[PDB]
Image 1: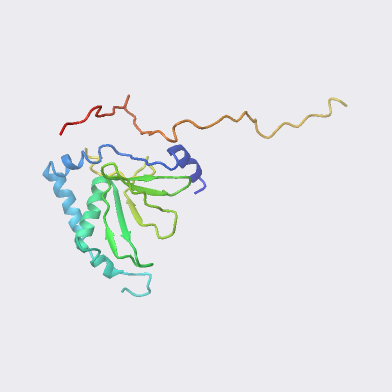
Image 2: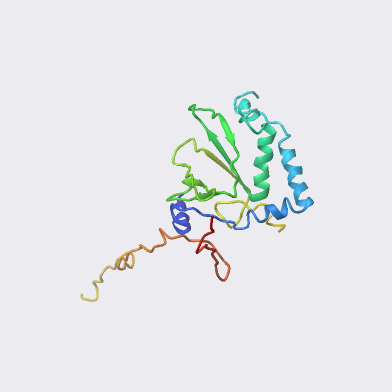
Length: 171
Length: 48
């Protein structure tokens, strides 16, 4: 945090850091191109969506109605098969939540990561995320407490904003 | 006694302040190790 004022001004304050250029040319050649890269992702994404979850920290194992039915489209397992299918492919999982209610948001949408980029800002954590499809942006805001995007990263040792995505290692 | 008195220097070597407006705030920067960078434009468009 004290080192936040020095890494963000060198990376560029208030701008979108795009990162990997071949994050989509590896998807169509390494996931729809060969069966081993196809099966290995679909093996894990169907497996991590199959393990159940328990609600601790409540002092007794019981939002479980949110995860089992996020939205009108994809089902509980369809949500995690798309979420883990982005972390294994591009190292970055994004989760939009719409909340007309003040707490416990209504829908969870897996924002796909290849059309998604961060902006660092002045200090520490990223200030916004830009969902850029076509030429059109969105500019979410993280300058508040509820923070409408969870950003799940895999481990990346040299970059400060993204994941490494084992498909990049086996390219 | 003139040798006994010694002036006190500043804490840090200070310099002239120069402006930091660099057109890098409005232009588009990319992180490209490659010995160059290419861009692809459409100087004209299709016809309908």
